[PDB]
């Protein structure tokens, strides 16, 4: 009947590799670059927009930096439509954990669940996996500042700075060169843009092609303040570092 | 290339399984006409019994979907029976949920959406029929809505379906540029049956016996088909003139 | 070929290869022969075994007190269709207090085989049955085919080199059907009938299996040392 | 092509190749006919005798539905016996819900929809039979023939199976000579004659005749098997025409 | 409620009250009880208004479907639909329905379905809470094959009594005449029958 | 048993001139025995205030219920939910469990940001909207507040006068009731800031 | 609670009182009972206050959808027939009693509908707790051929009689007139019968009457940079 | 039976493209041109009603639709695929956001729910992606006027003005020259007619052009006048007579 | 029913529960602990319906311990209370409820503060300086008001607790046969052997 049309996506190849996983990664190297630099007292998230025109509305726009709850944000690299389903079960799962324990969910648990959901899509069901990679940038009280990435495999690991999207080889080479561990949020701001000026496909880096975001311990009391920069604050930070 | 065996966008953007379905319809060499009167809608359809063994009356292509929406079908007759059984169920279901008689618009838009579902799922072939609903609506007066195996439907001042439709189409275009109205004017509905038959004789180039036509008239309050004597009466009145 | 993938496909001439292949499975099996008169019905069965140390496989299944069948071919499929007949023979005896007529049992198998080769993801059954039985209207002998067809016969064989015994029974048709009232002679006509199909493997007293049911005889099976009388 | 490998895939011609192969499975079967009498219907079937082992007149291939519809099919006997079995449930749930025996023009649609459903989906085979059914109800006699498309119509007379080219012509002689109406008693004689002539293609193996009829005047609207003196009187008329 | 239906020479006539009481207070004093469920197969409701209306909707839906597939329903049929819902759900729905109908073949016919769910063909029928008070009057005075002018007067007299003795009936009497000619509504105000 | 008088409590809310106030008592009983005096009935999401009286366990469930829905709301639309909308949300959530209700009687109070119009709303068990321009009351001594408030209230009070009224209203009704007392909390909501005052009242 | 509906030659007017109560306590002195299914089908509810508010919205949605899908003014008989089906599926636990009035192309209509599902057509219906006091007033002066003026005066009089003679009724009179081919006219607070006389002696306390223990400030904002 | 259509028809190809979705966008480039311009006090969206015959009446057919009382839509591509999406969207505004908040969704939230129907059409088993791109104009009180484009992959972006269809390349470059930020509603309409006159070869008059604005509020369609808390539709579709008037004033 | 007392001193929680178990007219067994250790710093005592107790204690103890293996991080005693409250609230709407009252005593090593929680069978959580359930809160709440101070040490609190039980011995009309006492504090969980 319909035996013929099956792609049989989920079987191994003779080498021991999952075909659909290897492709999804290649697809993800076409999406605009995203970079995370973790410092002692905060996290920077800078992502290079894709699609731009003098006729595109930019100020209200939001295509790569999404907020999950109070203290955790992500950056998307890949199919923005596919990701929008994985962002909605992340929020739901977060508040469901707040409903049952009365604590902000630990960063380790909210990562581990979105990787099980990715893994479970290559295990069975014959569906093509999501084409997404996340940079989970989050803060709990247990370990302080954390970074995580996941891949359409499911596998996830922690990083002090990492790149996904285009020129991850080129961007990862620069980042190893300049990273240091005494860094502060304002040095990391400077490094994240310095890496994006060199890897950019643009003839010149410009404020209207950036999505920028910090999570600082800074801000009143002990509480943590997440700040997705306005389009206008990015023009100021871009003259401050003197790239323009 | 499995795109000519199920409905997935071809490399070109087409849906080859749907473009094929249209050429499956035009094969019965039946030519259908539907024109509007002032207070009625006439539809005349060729009937062709091939062998003397088939009983003449059971062969038919006009169905009575409700009390005021008749539907003349063009295509292979099993798909028509399938499309007819399902349309009758909806005209009942409508009157049960909302308590008034399913207007024609609404029925044509329901079948359209039902057609679409079959070109979206990979496990049903589209229907191989063109459906032409005719009614005297309660609100909008005389109506015709012709629906396709893509899902497309649209209103009509008058329509023609079949292999030889090109002859009838261009004959209708000529008449409505002369008269400068959207509908055959003549007041009684017998004069509009006369008018329909005369444009069929011209288009196809051939005259009609009374066994070769099957006729359906929608006036407000009832839809009916005309018997072999009431057809004979029109035929003799056209030959007089 | 190309059309023998599934049973959903008619071939370009109309044949259903998956159903003609299932037929093959009965020509691999052992011969069994069935005949009947008006008073009694009889199955003579060649039991087959593997190597020496093997014991012979049972080819005769008791279905009820008045009905049983023998199988030829796939022994796992026979036990799935005889389980389904068992439930039917109870279902009749409890709800209508009525010994299930043989003519009906045949039409139930017919219907069950049809639904199983139309479904996508089924498989035709690969086994033949001779179903004998004695009801209100007398004795019957049915041949069941995996196609579905149930045919009522006076005698028949199925299996390997069946043709030898199928012929023998159409010459002797007038004589073994008139053997009424003597169960002993109807068994002897059937032992002869199975010796035409045998080429090698002379009968033994552990090789042969006989069932006989009739007007005055609940369904009984003779194995082992109980078939020393009929060789 | 490749438009034939699976069911309900259109070709460029519009043809549905799987259904066209199904018609070839009907043409392989044995011959059957139906005469629409003036007040009833007559059914006739050619049952090939394959062996002398077969018991005579116990493998009857005419099946009744409810208590006033005769069905007789050609092609693959299993496919049909499942179509009839299903027809019996549709008819018993009509008589349950409206408490009146199901009209014959209605019973025709319900069987068509069930066949037709097996050319929508691409995972169940089309049916490999053509059924000729009918009987008597409040309006009178109806005779229908059903193909593996789902296409059925009324017929003055119908025939399917291998010998159908012969029989369509012979049937036609009896409709031109009697516009008045071939009367019910006369049609049992004629049925046997037609089957005996259409049997000249299959004249290799002897056959057995079986007639049944549903008639308003004769059996009061029920369905019975013509038998005994009346079946024997017909068989004699048929042997007299071919010799 | 007090309803009756009476066959006669040319067809059938249905009669009904129009009072609908909830306790002692009269909620609505002009309630149509004679409802059309096809073009010549009418019915009369009595019992729990909520329950009969539900059964009449589903009958009017079944029969509109039945007409577009099988042709004209006989009156027998429409009766058996009513029956099938009353009897499957007899636990809750409390409905007593008279189905009167006219073909051209078999002229007038009356079926009554009491609370259990049991069709019964009768030459007249009565139901409702005020029926008890006219069982005697109806049985002496009925005659098969009355004149249309004579029947009307025989139903008008009966319900005149069924209103006078029962507190749960009253108001205008409606009558619906089912004949070959079609449907004709009649109405009789309380001054046309209380004076009598 | 009365599913509402197991725990008691009373909530009262008043408008003024460009400000609102919502206040309650802090007792939590299990019929005769008093258990705790720390139990608060008033919660805030964004700048909208919700008081909930009744069965104590459904106060805790229905507070963590509404914190869930509004957090999700605040992540999509990117602004705290307004009081006018939030009132439809309370109502729809309750009626969702029409059969076997939450035994509560929520009270909304806040100032709508766009317009500056102060806004209060009341509820009952199933969930109807009591709309008032005066004051909303709720709880087991809701009969006593209705009479109390109506005598005191004068339309348009300035924020520091409103604070006196809603005190006398709540203090008197608690000591005429056998399920309220043990302190009281009063919020004064203005657009810029919120000022919370704990009251010294009698411990009888 | 008192609700009347009076048909007249050119349209239909539906009037109510504004008093909503919860027990022997008057919860609200203005809460209108007139709801809006669709722009020319109005209805009003008696019985449980949460059933009539919720079940007009569950029919509001489905009737607005259906209105865009046909591209047509949504008939009254549509809402009447869809309400009936929802209330019968719960076997009359939902205690909702509505007067559904309105206009559409076919003409004016007016129905009542009881908890279980029984409906009534009428030329003038009343429903509610003081519905009996209203019913009397109608039976006295209603005639045919009422003009638009007389009917309003009639309807509002019936609601008045409910106010003076029933306890559950009170407060103000609301009206809504729907004519054929014009927009419905909602006359919110059409008649003030009784106003609250001014208090004999104003009551207003000095400041510092209340005794206080603490004061704190509650945070209602996103923390900011320092 | 055992229907085995669970495996999706879309699979990742060895080149890092999602095959079916690419093709979908070819068929969107064959659809008829449509464009939208966002101004200071409104949006306009317009298209050409392709009338296939003179017998056909494209009046009964619509390529612009009401989704809520304040959110319209227009489209490019497959007729059918459009009509069933407008019916899911009308439904899901009500079931999942209007009942349970009492308010019509804000424009940027509805688009999110519509972007979720596209996703499920390309993820789940046995379906093919939709053959359309929507432009969704709308107004809500906190973000003002907004215009959105939705793709058949699921992605949506907010545009200052934009075109999709056959002459999308020639239309987008003519909009960048004529667009600025000061545009009122009247001037943007006149820039919308000029841009459509390039891409339309045949008839160009009020009977064959469909044009609809999200603009100032209307209290004339309100329909139940006599209540200050309501404000009525912001969407108003310009009729045939109105459209010929802005061609005299061309 | 059966007595459970909880008093939170300056650096520990003390939980005291009765030995006796009364099935039938006999006192069947009178040494059986009525308390399950959840984790090395949280102790949960429980009392209520027959047999429901054991089932609702081992159930909770399984999820807390599946959570300590998963993260290698002992849940705070603040969390553990809201998880027991979540279950009890679900049970009241179910076909058959769980009538179990719990005192959760725990030493939070995060802030070096002990905490006591009371959840009753309806499902109401409240932080308390001392609590009880049943009829015990009727005899002791008036004695703890007079003597308890927040600065007491463990040695002092036990002398207050010896007095509370001596109040129950006079007025209670039921054997409970003295208590078992367990202390939760920063050093772990120990059992006071004496009365």
Image (cartoon, coloured by chain):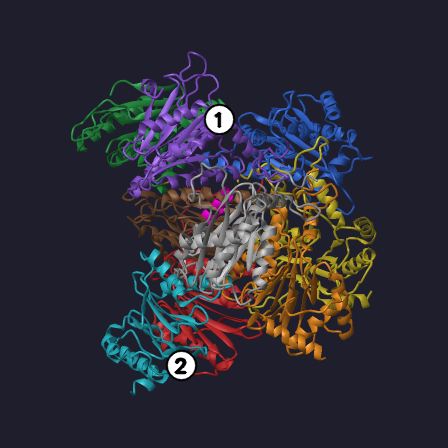
At a point 50% along the width and 36% down the height, the residue shown is C147
Q: Which chain gets the orange colouring?
A: B
- Of tags 2 and 1, the one toward the viewer is 1
Asked if the magenta segment contains residue I40, the reply would be no
Label 2, label 1: how many angstroms apart (C-alpha)? 89 Å
Q: Which chain gets the red colouring?
A: G
Left or right: I134, with F152 as reference point: left
Colour representing chain E: cyan
Subunit of label 2 = E
Question: Looking at the image, which is closer to me, B91 or D97?
Answer: D97
Query: Do the residues at pointers 2 and 1 share their chain?
Result: no
| Mark 2 closeness class: few <14, some 14–19, many ≥20 residues within 10 Å | few
Colour representing chain A: blue
Residue A217 position (above or below residue A16): below
| Residue pointed to by mark 2 | E186
Is residue C153 visible in the rendered structure shown here? yes
Name the secondary structure under disc 1. Answer: helix
Colour representing chain F: brown
Q: The N terminus of chain A appears in which quarter of the rendering?
A: top right
Q: Which residues are magenta?
A: D77-86
What is the number of the mark on residue C164? 1
Q: Which chain gets the purple colouring?
A: C
Q: Which chain gets the yellow colouring?
A: H
């Amino acid at each position: 009947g319909s035996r013929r049309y099956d792609s049989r996506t989920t079987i191994f190849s003779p080498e021991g590799r999952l075909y659909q996983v290897e492709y999804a990664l290649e697809s993800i190297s076409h999406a605009g670059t995203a970079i995370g630099i973790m410092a002692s007292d905060g996290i920077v998230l800078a992502a290079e927009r894709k699609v731009t025109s003098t006729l595109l509305e930019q100020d209200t726009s939001t295509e790569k930096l999404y907020k999950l709850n109070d203290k955790i944000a992500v950056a998307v690299a890949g199919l923005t439509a596919d990701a929008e389903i994985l962002i909605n079960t992340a929020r739901i799962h977060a508040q469901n954990y707040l409903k049952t324990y009365n604590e902000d969910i630990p960063v380790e648990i909210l990562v581990r669940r979105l990787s099980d959901i990715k893994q479970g899509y290559t295990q069975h069901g014959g569906l093509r996996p999501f084409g997404v990679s996340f940079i989970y940038a989050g803060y709990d009280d247990r370990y302080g500042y954390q970074l995580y990435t996941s891949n359409p495999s499911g596998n996830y690991t922690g990083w002090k700075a990492i790149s996904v999207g285009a020129n991850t080889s080129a961007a990862q080479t620069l980042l190893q060169m300049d990273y240091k561990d005494d860094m502060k949020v304002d040095d990391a701001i400077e490094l994240a843009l310095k890496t994006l000026s060199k890897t950019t496909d643009s003839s010149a880096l410009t404020y209207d092609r950036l999505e920028f975001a910090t999570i600082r311990k800074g801000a009143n009391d002990g509480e943590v303040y997440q700040k997705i920069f306005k389009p206008q604050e990015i023009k100021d930070i871009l003259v401050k570092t003197g790239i323009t | 290339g499995y795109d000519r065996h199920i409905t997935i966008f071809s490399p070109e953007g087409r849906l080859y399984q749907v473009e094929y379905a249209f050429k499956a319809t035009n094969q019965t060499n039946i030519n259908s006409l539907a024109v509007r009167g002032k207070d009625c809608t006439v539809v005349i359809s060729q009937k062709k019994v091939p062998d003397k063994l088939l009983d003449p009356t059971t062969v038919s292509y006009i169905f009575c979907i409700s009390r005021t929406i008749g539907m003349v079908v063009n295509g292979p007759i099993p798909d028509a029976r399938n499309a007819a059984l399902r349309a009758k169920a909806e005209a009942a279901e409508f009157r049960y949920k909302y308590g008034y008689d399913m207007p024609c618009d609404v029925l044509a838009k329901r079948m359209a959406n039902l057609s679409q579902i079959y070109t979206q799922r990979a496990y049903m072939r589209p229907l191989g029929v063109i459906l032409t609903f005719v009614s005297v609506d309660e609100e909008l007066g005389p109506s015709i809505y012709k629906t396709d195996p893509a899902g497309y439907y649209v209103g009509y001042k008058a329509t023609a379906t079949g292999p030889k439709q090109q002859e009838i189409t261009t004959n209708l275009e000529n008449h409505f540029k002369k008269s400068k109205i959207d509908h055959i004017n003549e007041e009684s509905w017998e004069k509009v049956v006369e008018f329909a038959i005369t444009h069929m004789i011209d288009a196809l180039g051939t005259e009609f016996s009374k066994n070769d036509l099957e006729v359906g008239v929608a006036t407000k309050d009832k839809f009916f088909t005309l018997s072999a004597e009431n057809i004979e009466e029109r035929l003799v009145a056209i030959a007089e003139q | 070929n190309n059309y023998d993938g599934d049973t959903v496909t008619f071939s370009p001439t109309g044949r259903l290869f998956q159903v003609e292949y299932a037929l093959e499975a009965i020509k691999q099996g052992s011969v069994t022969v069935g005949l009947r008169s008006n008073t009694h019905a009889v199955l003579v069965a060649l039991k087959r075994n593997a190597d020496e140390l093997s014991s012979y496989q049972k080819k005769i299944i008791k279905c009820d007190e008045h009905m049983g069948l023998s199988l030829a071919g796939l022994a796992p499929d026979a036990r799935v269709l005889s389980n389904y007949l068992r439930q039917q023979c109870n279902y009749s005896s409890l709800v209508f207090n009525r010994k299930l007529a043989v003519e009906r049992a045949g039409h139930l198998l017919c219907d069950k085989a049809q639904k199983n080769t139309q479904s996508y993801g089924g498989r035709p059954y690969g086994v033949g049955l001779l179903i004998i039985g004695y009801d209100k209207s007398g004795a019957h002998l049915l041949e069941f085919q995996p196609s579905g067809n149930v045919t009522e016969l006076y005698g028949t064989a199925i299996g390997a080199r069946s043709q030898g015994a199928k012929t023998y029974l159409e010459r002797t048709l007038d004589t073994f059907i008139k053997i009424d009232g003597n169960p002993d002679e109807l068994i002897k006509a059937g032992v002869e009938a199975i010796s035409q199909s045998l080429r090698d493997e002379s009968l033994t007293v552990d090789n042969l299996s006989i069932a006989i049911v009739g007007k005055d005889t609940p369904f009984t099976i003779y194995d082992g040392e109980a078939v020393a009388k009929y060789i | 092509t490749g438009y034939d490998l699976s069911n309900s895939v259109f070709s460029p011609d519009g043809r549905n190749f799987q259904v066209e192969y199904a018609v070839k499975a009907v043409e392989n079967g044995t011959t059957s006919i139906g005469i629409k009498c003036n007040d009833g219907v007559v059914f006739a079937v050619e049952k090939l005798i394959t062996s002398k082992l077969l018991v005579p007149q116990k493998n009857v291939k005419i099946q009744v539905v409810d208590r006033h519809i005769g069905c007789v099919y050609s092609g693959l006997i299993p496919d049909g016996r499942h179509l009839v079995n299903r027809g019996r449930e549709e008819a018993a749930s009509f008589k349950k819900l409206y408490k009146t025996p199901i009209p014959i023009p209605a019973f025709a649609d319900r069987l068509g929809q069930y066949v037709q459903a097996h050319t929508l989906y691409n995972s169940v085979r089309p049916f490999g039979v053509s059924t000729i059914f009918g009987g008597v109800d409040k309006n009178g006699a109806h005779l229908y023939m059903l193909e593996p498309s789902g296409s059925y119509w009324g017929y003055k007379g119908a025939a399917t199976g291998k010998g159908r080219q012969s029989a369509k012509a012979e049937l036609e002689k009896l409709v031109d000579h009697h516009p008045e109406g071939l009367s019910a008693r006369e049609a049992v004689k004629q049925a046997a004659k037609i089957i005996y002539l259409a049997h000249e293609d299959n004249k290799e193996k002897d056959f057995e005749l079986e007639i049944s009829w549903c008639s308003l005047s004769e059996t009061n609207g029920l369905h019975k098997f013509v038998k005994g003196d009346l079946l024997q009187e017909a068989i004699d008329f048929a042997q007299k025409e071919i010799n | 409620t007090s309803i009756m239906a009476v066959t006669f020479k040319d067809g059938v006539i249905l009669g009904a009250d129009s009072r609908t009481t909830t306790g002692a207070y009269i909620a609505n004093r002009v309630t149509d009880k004679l409802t059309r469920v096809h073009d010549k197969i009418w019915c009369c409701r009595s019992g729990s208004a909520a329950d009969t209306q539900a059964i009449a909707d589903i009958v009017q839906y079944h029969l509109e479907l039945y007409t577009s597939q099988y042709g004209t329903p006989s009156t027998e049929t429409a009766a058996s639909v009513f029956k099938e819902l009353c009897y499957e759900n007899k636990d809750n729905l409390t409905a007593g329905i008279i189905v009167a109908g006219y073909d051209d073949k078999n002229k007038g016919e009356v079926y009554t379905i009491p609370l259990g769910g049991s069709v019964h063909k009768l030459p007249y029928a009565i139901a409702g809470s005020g029926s008890t008070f006219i069982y005697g009057y109806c049985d002496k005075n009925f005659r098969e094959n009355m004149s249309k002018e004579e029947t009307v007067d025989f139903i008008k007299h009966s319900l005149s009594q069924a209103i006078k003795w029962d507190g749960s009936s009253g108001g205008v009497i409606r009558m619906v005449v089912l004949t070959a000619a079609g449907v004709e509504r009649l109405i009789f105000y309380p001054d046309e029958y209380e004076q009598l | 048993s009365d599913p509402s008088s197991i725990n008691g409590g009373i909530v009262v809310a008043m408008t003024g001139k460009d400000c609102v106030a919502i206040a309650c008592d802090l007792r939590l009983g299990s019929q005769s025995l008093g258990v705790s005096n720390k139990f608060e009935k008033i919660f805030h999401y964004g700048h909208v205030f919700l008081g909930i009286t009744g069965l104590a366990t459904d106060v805790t469930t229905l507070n963590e219920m509404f914190r869930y829905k509004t957090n999700l709301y605040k992540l999509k639309e990117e602004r705290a939910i307004e009081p006018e909308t939030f009132t439809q949300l309370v109502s729809s959530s309750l009626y969702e469990r029409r059969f076997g209700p939450y035994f509560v009687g929520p009270v909304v109070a806040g100032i709508n940001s766009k317009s500056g119009k102060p806004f209060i709303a009341g509820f009952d068990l199933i969930g109807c909207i009591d709309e008032a321009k005066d004051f909303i009351v709720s709880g087991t001594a809701s009969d006593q507040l209705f009479g109390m408030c109506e005598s005191l209230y004068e339309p348009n009070l300035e924020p520091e006068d409103l604070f006196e009224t809603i005190s006398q209203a709540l203090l008197n009704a608690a000591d005429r009731d056998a399920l309220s007392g043990w302190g009281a909390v009063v919020y004064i909501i203005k657009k810029d800031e919120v000022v919370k005052r704990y009251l010294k009242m009698r411990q009888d | 609670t008192t609700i009347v509906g009076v048909k007249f030659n050119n349209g239909v007017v539906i009037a109510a009182d504004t008093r909503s109560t919860q027990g022997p306590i008057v919860a609200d002195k203005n809460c209108a009972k007139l709801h809006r299914i669709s722009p020319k089908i109005w209805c009003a509810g008696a019985g449980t206050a949460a059933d009539t508010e919720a079940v007009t919205q569950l029919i509001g949605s489905n009737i607005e959808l259906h209105s865009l899908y046909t591209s047509r003014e949504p008939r009254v008989v549509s809402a009447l027939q869809m309400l009936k089906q929802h209330l019968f599926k719960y076997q009359g636990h939902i205690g909702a009693y509505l007067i559904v009035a309105g206009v559409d192309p076919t003409g004016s209509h007016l129905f009542s509908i009881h908890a279980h599902g029984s409906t009534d057509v009428g030329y003038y219906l009343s429903l509610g707790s003081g519905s009996l006091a209203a019913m009397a007033v109608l039976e006295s002066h209603w005639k045919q051929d009422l003009t638009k003026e007389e009917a309003i005066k009639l309807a509002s009089d019936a609601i008045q009689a409910g106010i003076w003679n029933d306890l559950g009724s009170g407060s103000n009179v609301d009206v809504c007139v729907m004519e054929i081919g014009k927009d419905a006219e909602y006359l919110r607070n059409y008649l003030t019968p009784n106003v609250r006389e001014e208090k004999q002696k104003s009551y207003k306390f000095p400041r510092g009457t209340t005794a206080v223990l603490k004061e704190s400030i509650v945070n209602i904002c996103d923390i900011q940079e320092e | 039976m055992t229907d085995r259509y669970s495996f999706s028809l879309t699979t990742f190809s060895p080149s890092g493209k999602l095959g079916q979705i690419d093709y979908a966008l070819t068929a969107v480039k064959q659809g008829v041109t449509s464009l939208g311009i966002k101004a200071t006090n409104g949006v306009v969206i317009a298209t050409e009603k392709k009338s296939s015959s003179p017998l056909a009446m494209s009046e009964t057919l619509s390529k612009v639709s009401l989704l809520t009382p304040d959110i319209g839509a227009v489209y490019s591509g497959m007729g059918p695929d459009y009509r069933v999406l407008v019916d899911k969207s009308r439904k899901v505004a009500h079931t999942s956001y209007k009942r349970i908040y009492g308010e019509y969704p804000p424009t940027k939230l509805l688009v999110s729910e519509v972007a979720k129907i596209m996703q499920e059409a390309t993820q789940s088993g046995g379906v093919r992606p939709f053959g359309v791109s929507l432009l969704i104009a709308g107004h809500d009180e906190f973000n003002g006027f907004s215009l959105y484009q939705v793709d058949p992959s699921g992605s949506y972006f907010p545009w200052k003005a934009t075109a999709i269809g056959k002459g999308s390349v020639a239309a987008k470059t003519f909009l960048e020259k004529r667009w600025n930020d000061e545009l009122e509603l009247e001037d943007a309409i006149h820039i919308a007619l000029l841009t459509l006159k390039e891409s339309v070869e045949g008839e160009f008059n009020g009977d064959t052009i469909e044009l609809a604005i999200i603009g100032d509020e209307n209290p004339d369609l309100l329909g139940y006048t006599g209540i200050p808390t309501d404000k009525g539709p912001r969407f108003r579709k310009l009729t045939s007579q109105e459209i010929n008037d802005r061609l005299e004033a061309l | 029913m059966d007595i459970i007392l909880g008093i939170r001193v300056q650096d520990s929680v003390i939980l005291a529960s009765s030995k006796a178990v009364t099935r039938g007219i006999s006192v069947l067994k009178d040494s059986d602990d009525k308390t399950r250790q959840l984790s090395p710093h949280t102790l949960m005592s429980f009392a209520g319906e027959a047999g429901d107790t054991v089932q609702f204690a081992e159930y909770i103890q399984a999820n807390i311990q599946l959570y300590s293996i998963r993260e290698d991080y002992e849940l705070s005693p603040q969390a553990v209370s809201s998880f027991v409250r979540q279950e009890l609230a679900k049970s009241i709407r179910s076909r058959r409820p769980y009538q179990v009252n719990v005192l959760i005593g725990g030493y939070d090593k995060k802030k070096n503060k002990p905490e006591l929680y009371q959840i009753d069978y309806l499902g109401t959580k409240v932080e308390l300086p001392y609590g009880a359930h049943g009829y015990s809160g009727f005899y002791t709440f008036s004695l703890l008001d007079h003597h308890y101070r927040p600065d007491m040490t463990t040695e002092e609190g036990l002398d207050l607790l010896k007095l509370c039980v001596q109040e129950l011995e006079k007025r209670m009309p039921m054997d409970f046969k003295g208590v078992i006492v367990k202390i939760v504090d920063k050093d772990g969980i120990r059992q006071v052997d004496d009365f």
